[PDB]
Image (cartoon, rainbow over all chains, first blue to last red; front, side, top):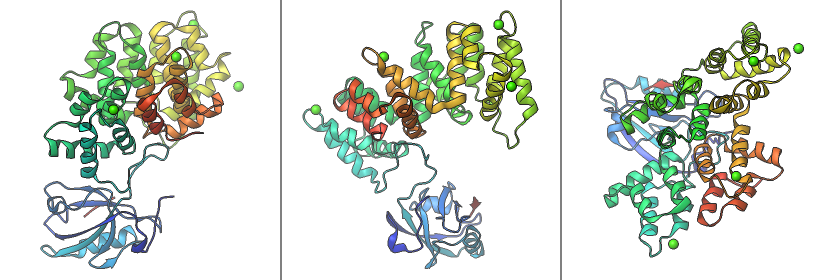
Length: 423
Length: 4
Ligand SMILES: [Ca+2]
Ligand SMILES: [Ca+2]
Ligand SMILES: [Ca+2]
Ligand SMILES: [Ca+2]
């Protein structure tokens, strides 16, 4: 349960006092929370060109402590909104805000927002570590792996503002090897990281299909819209065109369909009749007949919602002697088969999917560092705790333990911080 | 979620 108190003397972070004059379009910010009897009200967003943003003190996630010297900790959403609306135009409001409590963080991520966050202090310390004779990598790793992705963007902004140099460029020149790969990956936003991992996977027609498949099969609609937008910004070409240029056959049709990020959203009602019909269609399209009707498989597995397809795959076992994964291995081959196997795993149990990919990257000789690094970077704020839970349950030892055996040095220490702990 |  999120922390809550009605006493200001028990709040965690730092306090900001603001004075805003009401404009024609209000004070220019939105708030969330205050429905549960014990829930903070926090700043959801700030209207640009509005009083709150132009003042410069208010920030997203801040807890509203008091309004016009009345403490509003514990007050309902409706009571506080009424206070702001009753203020006439030109009158002012006095706000005390508390900065340190986060908003909208995943419950299953391993990397949490640092509470006493000071972007300027972090940039200063990173610069000192970069300029140290024989780079101080420990400080660089200790900081960046203990900050959320959003905070790393603030660190990079404060670093560029002080030194007039990009933080990623300075770290690229100071770090090397697998440690450099991890740190530079942490510095990108989730969409920037996936977009550049996708571009790298399509270096030629001899494509690292594993990486393309892994990203496109495991990303959600929301994540794929931002990837498609950011990919075109960074590389001035649509992601779909590069997939079309880099794939062929039914494998191409499947990757293009998934990358659109237009999967049907999770419905409120379970459609039991469509569940049975989809299961029969998957059976009729494959195991039941000679050959395979691949477009029917692509259509059902790319367009239906994930909760729907989980029940479809269970109902499919009623008609077919083999489950969906085994049916795929019997019906198709090559990149098409690998893509269907990854997609079905992502639908059925995405944390287990990443746990198996982590095991494969380390089990044998050496390491598939590219796979291991990308997963530890991209899932550390999504579902890393479920990935660790599935890993320890299946393999007996923790993901932490396997990372220790396969990697060494500051590289290992960074991966262990992204892991989050032993199991 | 309410605008102010
Ligand atoms: Ca050094
Ligand atoms: Ca068949
Ligand atoms: Ca049955
Ligand atoms: Ca291996």
